[PDB]
Amino acid sequence: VSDVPRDLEVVEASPTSIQISWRHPHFPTRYYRITYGETGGNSPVQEFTVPLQPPTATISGLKPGVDYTITVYAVTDGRNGRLLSIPISINYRTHHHHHH
Image (cartoon, rainbow, N blue to C red):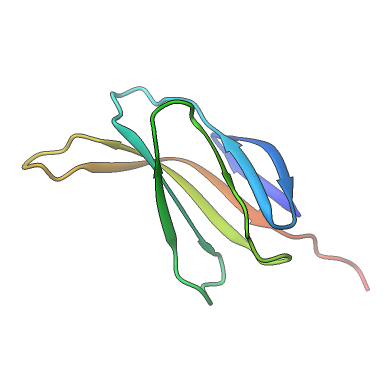
């Protein structure tokens, strides 16, 4: 496993799990939406929402040795009751190239 973060911390990880944390952004935020999907795209993207506090999530049940892209969205007020989802953080769940 190599977890490659952008604007988040990888707190804990295993072959099947990851615990990420991020910072509140520079604009008022209602809550966070976290998406994750196999990077190679054999399985569809899954989404869930978490409260504003704390800005930390753990995903488990990941397939061992399978790459995923994990995105953190800040969800905030838009116009006409349509919320805005602003991607603020990413983790790329990648794996070693193992020499053979």
